[PDB]
Length: 514
Ligand SMILES: [Zn+2]
Ligand SMILES: [Zn+2]
Ligand SMILES: [Zn+2]
Ligand SMILES: [Zn+2]
Ligand SMILES: [Zn+2]
Ligand SMILES: [Zn+2]
Ligand SMILES: [Zn+2]
Ligand SMILES: [Zn+2]
Image (cartoon, rainbow, N blue to C red; front, side):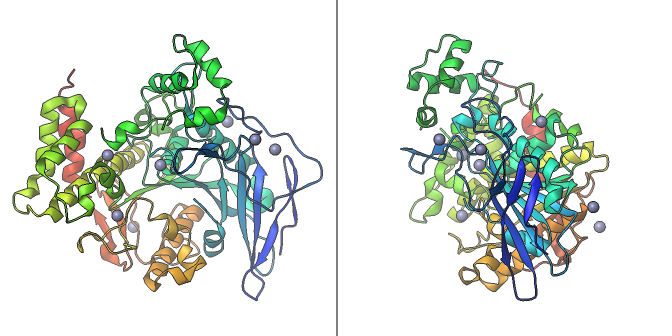
């Protein structure tokens, strides 16, 4: 009931077996399988040469080279394109034809992921992997000298390896689900939209991030390539000459070269390149016509970022004023000028007449950031996916479970990335740090997620679920709200549709100013 040495395209791989319980269940764990060669700075990934004998996949390998926590140093290595696999095993035979879920992490467009709980509770295979981030993942001139999107190609290389090789581990290669959060959710979305993945992906889950979020596509890469070159001493007059100089700069200097609202400081991210991303992502959804799709957000997703743009929200000691909010709103709506700043300010502060409390005003700032960074882009992606669906199902969720006491006792919510610990079963892996109801939420999310992996239907699979999750259509606009106490009223509809319509209809029709 164990895997032993596993035959892959590159050679034999040996993992470890961890016995779970006393009746014969276990899990096979593989860490550090290479899926591409050691990377070259600002060059596309390459096949990894095969190896002789048996590769011992016992330890996580280094991550890709990236800036530390205080932007003063680096960690990781150029030899970083590795993946890890968790295979659950029963008492009788070794597993076969299991659904495969590939996690793409986020954190680099705006750390420890262990697949054991999802795999064993959901009877699926979980894959994690590294891709290149920052300047080394996304530096670009916008043309063929330095086309960008290296990190997206890394992700695609890992998915293609899984398609070629996972059957030997007991996986079904025709049933691959991608799932990921923040940048990883946006990357999941971008992978479903790229022609590169045709035939590779069965379904996908975007958590707090889609290709349409405004922090995903850099439309002025050449401006950012120049700021890096000028700091590392490269010339900036020619594209082909700056690019080559960047390609032979110390990769640590490229990484540390670079250290107004938070969104204006999104730099080294995917670009529309005419190749991996052939067009604006909004025009690509026919590529996902047959990829089942969950997308969702957290109901306080924007709170961390509103806190950076306006620290006054996190202390009843200080106040947020109409003038502070107008300034924030005005910088987001610049391309529509004074007129666009006012219509937006007016719509969001309409409730301030009846409720002028700092609780309501500070909540409005959070809602504004949640809407424009996460919720509205996600609602547009759901509609776009639904509109282009042939066989694909579409599902929407809102994650609202609090993990901690709020600033105001009515700010019941989940902040950005709060969803990860529940999806990954941390309340069961380290239960002393968690409450009973936390395990209730985690149990339900793993059930929905891995049912969806197995069948494309979050309600149908190996696990019972608390409430029926109705597929999204243009007519029902339904979403599942995920809380510690779920029942039939957890299926809701029309989330903040007045603000959806404001952004998609009213704001779009206003003239562009210069
Ligand atoms: Zn190697
Ligand atoms: Zn090295
Ligand atoms: Zn089979
Ligand atoms: Zn991110
Ligand atoms: Zn390819
Ligand atoms: Zn901001
Ligand atoms: Zn918070
Ligand atoms: Zn139904």
